[PDB]
Length: 64
Image 1 (cartoon, rainbow, N blue to C red):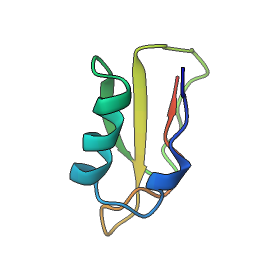
Image 2: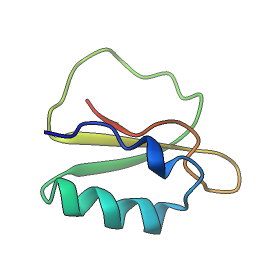
Image 3: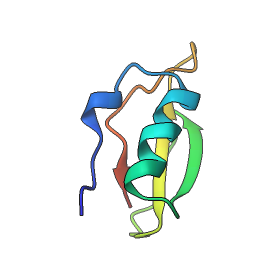
Image 4: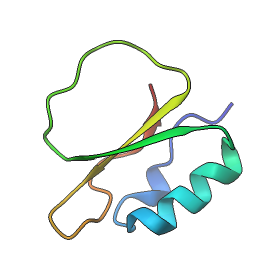
């Protein structure tokens, strides 16, 4: 189980989702502005995408 997609840093949302869903077809993908304060709960189904103002992935996407 691959749980991080560092190779997607700098990619647009459409592109990132396409790769993530190949690896984890039933992933719950959420998009949030980078810098958003989140809680520490661990959700194995989830992959949060932190994006910058150009709507590009700003941090390494990971399961949690």
